Image (tube, coloured by chain):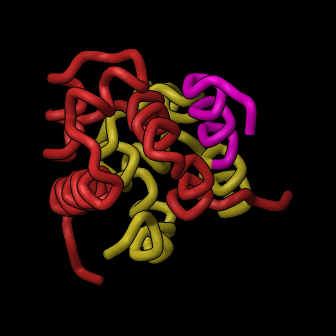
Chain colours: A yellow, B red
């Protein structure tokens, strides 16, 4: 991939948005589940998010089982 | 897999650290390659990092594709 880190972060944000839509959830619903502000979820879907917050969002979508496979050892 | 988001971020920090060590790189050298501050790398290895910065660190370690195991591509 010949892409900047910020552009790839935006692509990951889009994947998070798609995962959410596939689960028929709104940003407000994801925020309520994770116990965070709706604005924080909105920002995450733009690629602007802290790692622990992103993980909390993913846990709200039941999408953290793959993380065991991320740079493991 | 019953763990908190904070704990999991810290576990990812430790994985970033061991990926770096396996490549014989220092924190200073990763920062240099990625064009960021040393302290930013130090904090990332403790699990304190923004998504774009984590990606830049992965790119410095030639592990960019691993991001697809953090959030896979999604169909409609």
Q: How many marks?
A: 0
Q: Which segment is the magenta one?
A: A1-15
Q: In which quadrant of the rendered image does the N terminus of chain A lie?
A: top right
B37 falls in the magenta region: no
Task: Residue at the far bottom: name it.
Answer: B1
Q: Which percent across, then down, holds residue B60?
A: 46, 36
Q: Is B1 drawn above or below residue B26 in the view shown?
A: below
Q: From the viewer's perspective, is B76 left or right of A15?
A: right
User: What's the magenta bit mostly, secondary-structure-wise?
Assistant: helix
**Which residue lies at the image location 21% right of the left edge and 62% below the top edge?**
B11
- The picture quadrant where one finds residue B35 is top left
Q: In which quadrant of the rendered image does the C terminus of chain A lie?
A: bottom left
Q: From the viewer's perspective, is A11 left or right of B21?
A: right
- The picture quadrant where one finds residue A23 is bottom right
A11 falls in the magenta region: yes
Whether residue B5 is visible to the viewer of this picture, yes or no, is no
**Which residue lies at the image location 45% right of the left edge and 57% below the top edge?**
A58
Q: Which percent across, then down, holds residue A70?
A: 45, 66
């Amino acid at each position: 991939k010949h892409v900047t880190a910020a552009a790839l972060a935006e692509e990951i944000g889009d994947r998070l948005k798609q995962a959410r839509l596939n689960r028929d959830l709104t940003q407000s619903e994801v925020a309520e589940i994770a116990g965070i502000a709706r604005k924080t979820v909105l920002n995450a879907e733009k690629g602007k998010v802290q790692l622990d917050i992103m993980i909390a969002i993913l846990m709200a979508l039941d999408l953290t089982e793959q993380i065991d496979l991320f740079i493991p050892k």
